[PDB]
Amino acid sequence: NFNFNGLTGTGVLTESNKKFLPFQQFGRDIADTTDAVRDPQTLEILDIT
Amino acid sequence: GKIQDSLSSTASALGKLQDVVNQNAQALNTLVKQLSSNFGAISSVLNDI
Amino acid sequence: DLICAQKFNGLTVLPPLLTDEMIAQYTSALLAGTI
Image 1 (cartoon, helix red, strand yellow):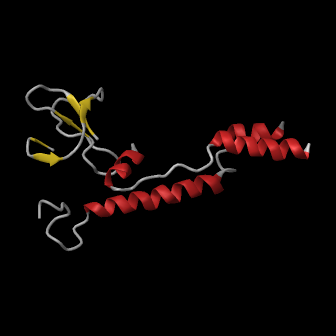
Image 2 (cartoon, each protein chain N blue to C red):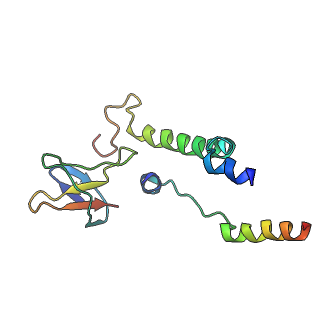
Image 3 (cartoon, one colour):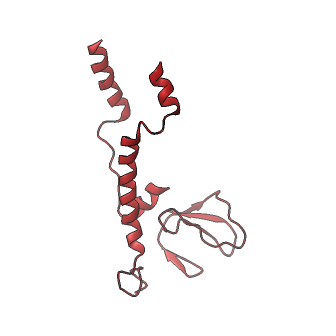
């Protein structure tokens, strides 16, 4: 289970190579799920499966 | 030999198949989007209600 | 991916009992028998 910046869900957090634009927060998939998030404290692209 | 030239550039001849694959993922998509709809309730997130 | 979000809400896509390599044996056999 997790919360990032108030965003909540449950998934398997991994290292991911998808590349955000700096101001961004979430990633998302076609289905309006929350697919990928960026760790606030250490910026890194974390998948959510 | 004519057959293989047709397929080489023909996207349409498979329209029958391509439609079937589409229409499923279509209704599959729409099925998913319905998880984001309020349906009259105050939110579409289960826990946030 | 599309399958992933689907896979995530309870939507699962079971595998077709016959893999494409199997279908390609049938459509080989029928095709090799007819010849």
